[PDB]
Length: 90
Image 1 (cartoon, one colour):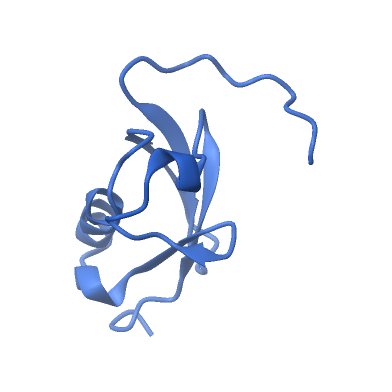
Image 2: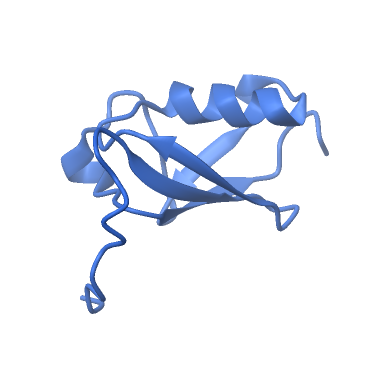
């Protein structure tokens, strides 16, 4: 496993995540450890003016579901998120 390198510590009830799009567009969102895909997808899709379902979010190369638990998403302070090119965006 990769070295922990110490988390940011910048959290409380929610954690930080850097969403990186295929457009090379990184955006910093605050979400919970157990946050559902809708929270981010709705949020990102909204800021970009794109259909929510047209946005596809993947964590570490696996798709983020609203059913996924914080255990399995293992997200933490300022973690990274991968986004694939939206359907409507092209």
